Length: 77
Image (cartoon, rainbow, N blue to C red; front, side, top):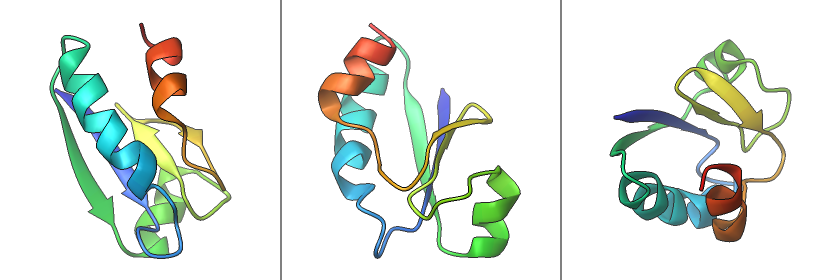
């Protein structure tokens, strides 16, 4: 349900929030599909200015530092 994009993958520590996001996003009561975007062409297209950009449902709010598990629940709840 929730379209979540992870820009960076490699150097980008999105890996942490990546796992937390899947369980929380889906568990919160809405499944989410996490597709990685290994290419700045796609990264910048998102709108983020940092590497570890995270755009959900077409809205990026994480750049240069992926969110935390506790942050997700607090951001959504």
